[PDB]
């Protein structure tokens, strides 16, 4: 699983000490954190391509904080895809609270950019503006997260036309395909370095892709000092990492889904005041189980076209699913509903020409076996979707490097049974749908749970004991 990018420095250099940062950055992070800072002060821009799940953002936060204790942060810009925008806020506010940030959506409006340490924004939110160009930002981070695939375009011309003093770029894996993107990013980070696009492709792209281990090695050589990339499989790193890393993957609902949600929300209320008793615990639990399906995929209700475009989960899943693939992982996707499972299998199975053994309850032991066997042994099989309700018939998922909870998991006994993260470290993803019971319940639980952990049981159940006042708080869609 070779895919590690070097940049000499692991013997000395300024192993900076994270500043006001609530966390114990594994050694490999304190380094990256520092290396970036180093190259930044030196005046070079760099790309951090560590496998998704090793927290390039935390390191980037540190890079941000250490540039605070030096009067080189206020103001900095971070251009991330809507999706990750939550992850960012999630982490600044938490890890580096002492750092002022603010999202920058549509129209100009109230500007205090210069007064804010960092400001968040989307590529699009750039493509149509001016407000920012005026600003002279210290840092300018381009977070090309696992976002779809086409990142380049007139967008870079916009970015690559701003005013920074420091430049970082968080990305997936320098895939030999990314070549043409490599020019765009390297340029952004270090302008001129590669010349012109025309020039680039001409002597690098067309040849390398056309099989030229010559210009290939060369290009690698020339950029080597500006790209740092650690691998979840790097022996040196397998160690510093926990058995399981937990990440929250956010997704935003399509306007269809959004509609179906608000609707299906009003329909439980405009028909609840009346009913009551266990004829409310059944009614509520019914709505919930529809909202959950809406977010998963509306084709689950309106029937119809089972496409990626109709589901925000599916879109995000697809991105995440894809980077993990490039990082050479083996993914396991779990879904509450059997049909969402088939949809997932289909979409993936089709869109990537590859088998996606699907495992669900009703299925002879032989199959569950042959399927899980197919996923375990066969290195060709890289996915497995599972829709199981039982405690754990007989699921052996030790081969999984990554796991996605398509449906909100509301467990250790479960992970143990399925053998997740037993004989390999494993990264686990929880899909969250912004402005949804999926998000709010995620909130109320971490509230205390000193009354919810020992007492109350599984997620679905109790959500119904909620008295209208808060039920209308938790489930009510929330988009400002
Ligand atoms: Hg790169
Ligand atoms: Hg963003
Ligand atoms: Hg979603």
Image (spheres, rainbow, N blue to C red):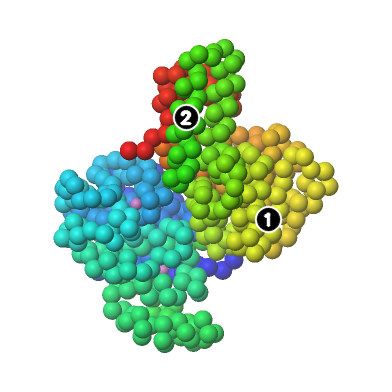
Report which residue position mark 2 lands on.
265
Instruction: Tell me: 251 left or right of 186.
Output: right
Q: Secondary structure at mark 2?
A: helix
Separation (CA) of disc 1 from disc 2 = 34 Å
Say whether marks 1 and 2 touch (CB < 8 Å): no
Q: Residue at x 71, y 34 (%)?
A: 390
Quarter-of-image position of residue 299: top right
Q: Quadrant of the N terminus?
A: bottom right
Asked if ligand 3 lies within 8 A of label 2, the reply is: no
* Camera-nearest residue between 314 and 37: 314
Q: Is residue 249 above or below residue 126?
A: above
Residue 101 point in image, percent of width and height: 26, 46
Q: Residue at x 19, y 47 (%)?
A: 109
Residue 287 point in image, percent of width and height: 54, 28
Q: Residue at x 65, y 64 (%)?
A: 353
Disc marking residue 345: none
Q: Is residue 187 above or below residue 256?
A: below
Q: Is any part of residue 84 visible from this angle?
A: yes
Quarter-of-image position of residue 154: bottom left
Q: Residue at x 32, y 58 (%)?
A: 124
Q: Quadrant of the C terminus?
A: top left
Q: Is residue 457 above or below residue 137?
A: above
10 Å neighbourhood of mark 2: few (<14), some, or many (≥20)?
some
Report which residue position mark 1 lands on.
356
Q: Secondary structure at mark 1?
A: loop
* Camera-nearest residue between 294 and 212: 294
Q: Is any part of residue 13 visible from this angle?
A: no
* Camera-nearest residue between 119 and 422: 119
Instruction: Tell me: 385 left or right of 62.
Output: right
Residue 270 point in image, percent of width and height: 46, 22
10 Å neighbourhood of mark 1: few (<14), some, or many (≥20)?
many
- Which comes before the other along the chain, label 1 or label 2? 2
């Amino acid at each position: 699983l070779v895919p590690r990018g070097s940049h000499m420095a692991s013997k000395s250099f300024q192993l900076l000490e994270p500043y006001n940062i609530k966390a114990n950055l594994r050694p490999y992070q304190i380094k990256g954190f520092s290396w970036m800072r180093f190259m930044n002060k030196l005046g070079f821009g760099i790309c951090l391509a560590d496998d998704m799940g090793l927290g390039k953002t935390l390191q980037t936060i540190a890079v941000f904080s250490d540039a605070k204790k030096e009067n080189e942060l206020t103001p900095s810009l971070v251009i991330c895809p809507l999706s990750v925008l939550k992850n960012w806020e999630e982490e600044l506010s938490k890890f580096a609270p002492h750092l002022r940030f603010a999202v920058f959506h549509e129209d100009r409006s109230k500007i205090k950019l210069e007064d804010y340490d960092i400001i968040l924004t989307t590529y699009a939110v750039l493509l149509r503006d001016t407000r920012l160009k005026e600003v002279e930002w210290k840092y300018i981070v381009i977070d090309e997260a696992q976002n779809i695939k086409n990142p380049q375009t007139k967008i870079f011309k916009a970015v690559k036309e701003l005013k920074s003093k420091y430049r970082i770029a968080l990305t997936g894996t320098p895939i030999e395909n990314k070549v043409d993107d490599l020019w765009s990013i390297m340029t952004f980070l270090n302008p001129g370095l590669l010349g012109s696009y025309s020039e680039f492709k001409s002597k690098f792209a067309t040849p390398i892709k056309k099989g030229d281990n010559m210009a290939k090695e060369e290009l690698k050589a020339i950029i080597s000092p500006f790209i740092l990339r650690r691998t979840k499989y790097d022996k040196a790193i397998i160690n510093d990492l926990p058995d399981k890393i937990e990440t929250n993957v956010y997704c935003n609902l399509t306007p269809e889904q959004a509609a179906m949600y608000k609707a299906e929300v009003e329909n439980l209320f405009n028909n609840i005041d009346s009913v009551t008793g266990i004829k409310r615990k059944g009614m509520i639990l019914s709505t919930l189980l529809k909202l959950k399906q809406i977010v998963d995929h509306p084709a689950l209700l309106k029937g119809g076209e089972q496409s990626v475009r109709r589901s925000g989960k599916m879109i995000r899943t697809m991105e995440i699913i894809e980077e993990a693939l490039d990082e050479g992982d083996k993914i396991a996707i779990f879904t509450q509903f059997v049909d969402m499972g088939k949809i997932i299998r289909n979409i993936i199975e089709k869109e990537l020409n590859t088998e996606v053994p699907f495992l669900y309850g009703e299925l002879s032991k032989k199959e569950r076996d042959d399927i899980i066997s197919k996923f375990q042994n066969n290195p060709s099989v890289k996915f497995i979707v599972l829709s199981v309700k039982a405690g754990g018939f007989g699921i052996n998922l030790t081969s999984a490097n990554r796991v996605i909870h398509f449906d909100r998991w509301w467990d250790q006994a479960t992970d143990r049974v399925y053998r997740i993260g037993q004989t390999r470290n494993v990264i686990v993803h929880k899909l969250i749908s912004v402005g949804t019971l999926e998000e709010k319940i995620d909130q109320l639980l971490a509230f205390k749970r000193s009354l919810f952990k020992d007492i109350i049981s599984s997620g679905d159940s109790w959500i119904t004991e909620l008295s209208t006042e808060e039920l209308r708080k938790v489930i009510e869609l929330s988009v400002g």
